[PDB]
Amino acid sequence: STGSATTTPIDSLDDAYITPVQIGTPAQTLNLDFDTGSSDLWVFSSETTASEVDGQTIYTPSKSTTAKLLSGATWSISYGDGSSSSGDVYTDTVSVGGLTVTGQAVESAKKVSSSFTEDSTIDGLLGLAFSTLNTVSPTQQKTFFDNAKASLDSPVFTADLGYHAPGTYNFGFIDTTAYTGSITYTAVSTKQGFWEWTSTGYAVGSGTFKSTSIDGIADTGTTLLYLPATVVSAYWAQVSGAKSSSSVGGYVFPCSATLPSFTFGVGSARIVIPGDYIDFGPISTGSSSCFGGIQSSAGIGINIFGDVALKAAFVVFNGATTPTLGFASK
Ligand SMILES: O[C@@H]1CNCCOC1
């Protein structure tokens, strides 16, 4: 089997991408944030504290003939931005882009943090990291991808994120029309439960390539690119007036600047992030100071190849017994 679903930016800054997902019988369609950096599928629901729901579409298991309470199971998760949610668990039929999984754990939120409440466009998350990160207790649950994996033609999914434009998540096949050149595959470590890999280095603009190993994770659920302070300082040093601002919480630059590209290495291959991708616009409406798309990972503990990097590539998440990550230009 295979699935193919369009993913769409939630706003004009590509802060996140939402993908329609069908849950239950008859289908209830929710727009979920596909997140290769976590492993829970959770949704706003009829159980979510009313004051914490503001415009989201909710899952109502009582209206689904295939929903069953997973008795005694609870879940609680916190994300890298400090957001969080928790609740209980149903099993139900879940379909993405024509690909159907029965008995999927659908985690129903009883509580969500304000950042989720304030974002009316995201109805929940669909985790695509390894199931060892799933937070359901006392019986840990499998991701949509892990459940689907047996039925898939190939144990892969691909992320093809758009720049200010819709993109595609495919399951079970690699669309050879969706990229140019060849795909370069690189080893993945699952030891921390992430799609963790090692970049072979970087270049700033037309500068020479610096060969250096950078361990990081491929994370569709993170907006920006977070790299070691040495790397990020070398990048912003090439932008007149750029600086790190503690008040703003990262690198800012004059909106009048032209940003250089940023290249990262995948084995012997090179993925080039255009300068425009790194511009996240005025820090507040009307400001002449703009927020940078490349930021330091120093306060995080881990380097993160977020949307800023991933949208510059066609990315293959290979969930074979020996998992790998593939990157191609597009
Ligand atoms: O908000 C980000 C999304 N990715 C999962 C881990 O970090 C949290």
Image (cartoon, rainbow, N blue to C red):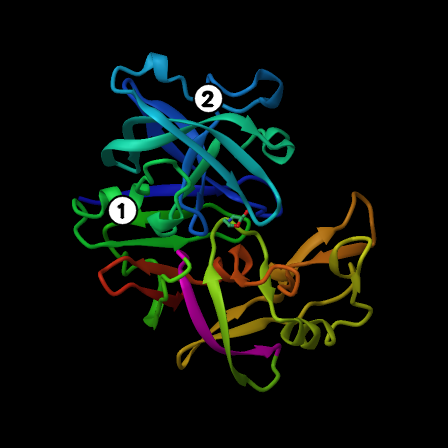
Picture layout, residue 178 above or below residue 55: below
Query: Which residue is at the front of the view, 227 or 286?
Result: 227
Say which amino acid is labelled 2.
Answer: Ser
The residue wearing badge 2 is 45
Q: Residue at x 34, y 54 (%)?
A: 158
* Mark 2 neighbour class, 10 Å CA radius: few under 14, some 14 to 19, many 20 or more: many
Q: Which comes before the other along the chain, label 1 or label 2? A: 2
Magenta residues, as a range? 193-205
Q: Secondary structure at mark 1?
A: helix
Quarter holding residue 116: top right
Say which amino acid is labelled 1.
Answer: Asp
Between the residue at mark 1 and the residue at mark 2, the CA separation in whole angstroms equals: 23 Å
Q: Which mark is residue 146?
A: 1
| Residue farthest top in this picture | 63
Q: Position of residue 200 (x, y in %)?
A: 46, 79
Q: Residue at x 40, y 44 (%)?
A: 127
Q: Position of residue 121 (x, y in %)?
A: 55, 32
Picture layout, residue 207 above or below residue 298: below
* Screen quadrant of the N terminus: top left
Q: Residue at x 83, y 49 (%)?
A: 287
Q: Secondary structure at mark 2?
A: loop
Q: Residue at x 50, y 31 (%)?
A: 86
Query: Which residue is at the front of the view, 185 or 255?
Result: 185
Picture layout, residue 143 above or below residue 198: above
Is residue 202 a member of the stretch shown in magenta? Answer: yes
